[PDB]
Amino acid sequence: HWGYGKHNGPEHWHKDFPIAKGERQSPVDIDTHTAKYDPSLKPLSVSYDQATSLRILNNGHAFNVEFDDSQDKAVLKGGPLDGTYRLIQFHFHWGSLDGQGSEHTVDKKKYAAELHLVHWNTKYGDFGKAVQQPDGLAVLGIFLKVGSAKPGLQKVVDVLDSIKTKGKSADFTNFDPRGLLPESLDYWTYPGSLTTPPLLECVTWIVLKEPISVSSEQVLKFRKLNFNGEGEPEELMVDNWRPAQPLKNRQIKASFK
Ligand SMILES: O=C(O)Cc1cccc([N+](=O)[O-])c1
Ligand SMILES: [Zn+2]
């Protein structure tokens, strides 16, 4: 099955998921000089005051911080979006070294990591129905750079020892994702896809301009996770990022001058 190795990594995904070579794949390089300011874009509305995290999961590709999405409790709206999108999970992508890890790039710059907050359009009722629609998901992407620690991330880091290997989960209640957000909500937006199989072309991407800072110690604990299951040969969970894909016939719009 798919992964991030030599034999099963991004460059192979198209064999099982031909949409890998589609017209609206993600991530992309954001060319800041050609992304045009769009005055018609709205401020993004991130309403996470009632978010109810439940659990953290090692799915063998990343770890997912999961939310109760059975009511409108943590929603993303505004920005480029029409309607209301409910938070279901967040996860990250990261590198073996601080010089790579992000999926999106900014003028070809790779950040150490990228956080993806995944939301589904309530007009489709559930996640599985939403991913079948071109406006089904809104993913908020946030770059991580290594410097100062992110206090709000530390709860996540400290639980990772308990989900070292694929298929492990742990209770993870009361975690507030507001602690993961940067000061500014300036963003770029474009139409794209999931960045893992099945690579469905269902996402409005909203990539924040301002990275968060995490410490070397924090990212080092991401890199102690394992792709393998308990008791199998250890292969560190690192470089679980898809590289930039062709922009094709897309425009990247900026919310800011
Ligand atoms: O389980 C999976 O890899 C598919 C999936 C599910 C939810 C979000 C995703 N994304 O690319 O942001 C991908
Ligand atoms: Zn992701």
Image (cartoon, helix red, strand yellow):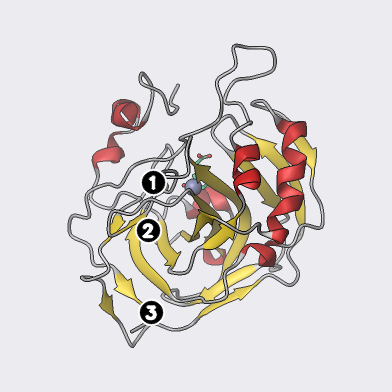
CB atoms of marks 1 and 2 within 8 Å = no
The mark nearer the N terminus, 3 or 2, is: 2
Residue 165 visible in rendering: yes
Mark 1: few/some/many CA within 10 Å (<14, 14-19, 20+) = many
Helix, strand or loop at label 3? It is loop
Quarter the C terminus occupies: bottom left
Instruction: Write down the residue under mark 3.
Output: 255
Quarter assignment of residue 179 = bottom right
> How far apart in space, not on screen, are marks 3 and 2 (Cα)?
21 Å
Instruction: Write down the residue under mark 2.
Output: 134
Residue 219 is marked as: none
Q: Residue flagged by tag 3: what amino acid is it?
A: Ser
The mark nearer the N terminus, 1 or 2, is: 2
Between marks 3 and 1 in the image, the one whose residue lies nearer the viewer: 3
Q: Residue flagged by tag 1: what amino acid is it?
A: Leu
Residue 200 is marked as: 1
Residue under the image location 47 percent in, 36 percent down: 240
> From the viewer's perspective, is residue 166 above or below residue 174?
above
